[PDB]
Image 1 (cartoon, rainbow over the protein chains, first blue to last red):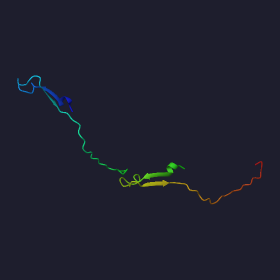
Image 2 (image 1 turned 135 degrees about the vertical axis):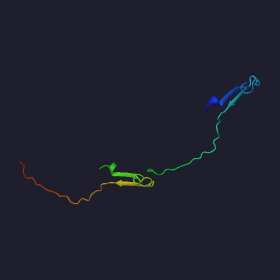
Image 3 (image 1 turned 45 degrees about the vertical axis):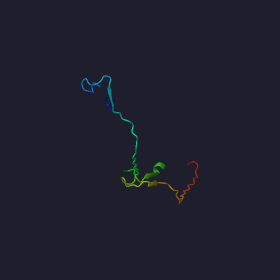
Length: 53
Length: 53
């Protein structure tokens, strides 16, 4: 949808309070869309027999 | 005379009103020319006797 807003990387400094976050710790949030299984295909056949309608 | 315009085939959809014609019904018009009997031969003999007329 938006790879820029789906994957975010923050340091531990911008997640934890002031002077509490530790250096070298990162927080990666990834909002991805995996393939789905595919459960049912509801097919609705509608035979058309008329030519002038 | 014209075999294309003498033999015409229409579906029932292009003959009946909208959504009224039934599928699988055809209308064949054939305007043919049958042999005629042959009733009389009016023969008109005209003997010609002159050479310079």
